[PDB]
Image (cartoon, rainbow, N blue to C red; front, side, top):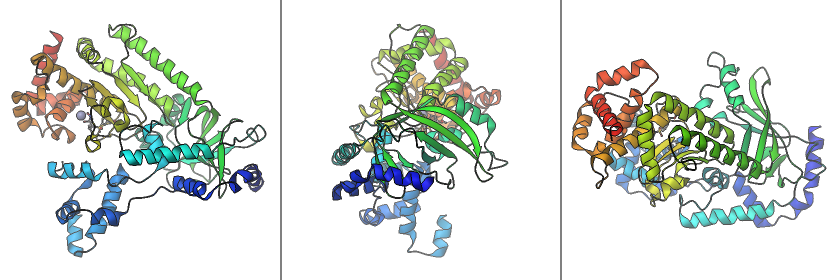
Length: 500
Ligand SMILES: COCc1cccc(S(=O)(=O)N(CC(C)C)[C@@H](C(=O)NO)C(C)C)c1
Ligand SMILES: [Zn+2]
């Protein structure tokens, strides 16, 4: 019985609940309901030239919510003028982006669970204001102290706990086409099998909030987790039949099936709570294995640390399994000599291929070279010349690209750009796209390739490189055709690098 099971759990935690102080309850409430920014106070703090700038700016050219909040911000600023003006109003200026980069630090909500997920538990990551960073730390530590009572040896194997979830949260890449296009009540059997094949374990770095009784799905809640706790899993009762689980727990995926609820298809994920260290072990074992493979394959020292698994979140095992596929497509589409030469260069600078489910501003390969948070970047992928590293963020959705394999190759094009400029002058060590020859090439052919390739010389080069190494024959030819100077320039650098 649903209501019986509910009361039985509430009872188990009744003394715990009644013992909560005023600050303890408010802390638990603040966690469930994050404190949103005050858009009135934000707008008030802007100069009226910045308001006009924020009024007419196309904000999506830069999170979706950040753009949605800014659009919520813009709409609130725009609701004082004409109807005709608003209907009319419906890359960036370097004045515009430079403005948004500083505005991003003022619109961040105080969200404990989000701070944990983004950092993967590494809350000392210098990606937010120090004072706020210390505030999260106090709350998190205090919540840890609150969640001290375990589920117990009696209840752990007599109950199931449930969690409805949006697919895009795990990976927005597969979430785009896991629902059948022809029939949205159906799940694409193809993607499901791959999804199921690579999900063997999961990690929760924040506080999971689960339902005692299964709640009917909302709009984009196509994932329905069924969780069995372990006897010493620490938790707390929340009002309206919910449990808050301790942070830093591991989940073994026991079964992934397609089920039917109300003539619509959902994915059920059965998972059992295990020690997080047990899963961290499997991750570290996988990290050492993939490095052993690629050290031999690349002609590198046996113990070279090149590939990093910075994995802390709910779709952990796929981040691991995707890195294998990504590097394989990378190996297949790029000359082995171009690869070895450039990779050895990265290793000289103690570089890494970082595959992670935490946000890039919280990746040490970035923030140790980027002190200003307004210069810190989150995106699907990145190349950081200061650390000679490629960073790839699994969960997020990427701009204009299909899979992550194309994303990595694009990032590798950045390393090629780097290495080309180094060989050109080993004392200056600048990017070859900063050379005047390529600059003029960009001024001409810079608008022929992909939309994002129009951003700058470095980006144009990377996009060009990616398309020149695509599996699609047509897109290789488009570069050779629409950007012949760029096409030849890269082949020049590739020849240059190999013959070193
Ligand atoms: C499905 O994955 C797609 C994907 C893979 C890798 C990176 C990204 S990206 O973040 O959108 N991205 C631009 C794209 C076109 C490479 C970043 C970038 O120029 N890196 O060097 C750019 C925003 C800084 C997306
Ligand atoms: Zn790029």
